[PDB]
Length: 99
Image (cartoon, rainbow, N blue to C red; front, side):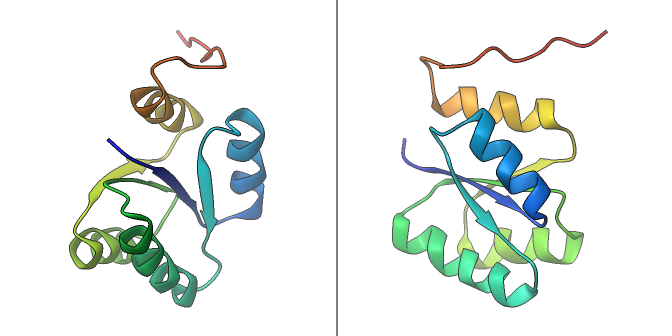
């Protein structure tokens, strides 16, 4: 029970998630220096649930172990969409269904 931080490696992914979900906070990682700023950001905000969208595996396991938090490894929009609804019971959107 707390904040959901969506961490992205690309501005295109950031502005996407922020438009779809103004109800979550998003961190941009262009270099590992920003990923370190994420490790700090998490602990200072007290974030238990942290999404890692399109990140490197070295950065995945690194943020995981050092921040000591639940990592949601996202490779598709739909995955992120479900993780947001996990924290946000009363969702303000409609997740698109695929087949």
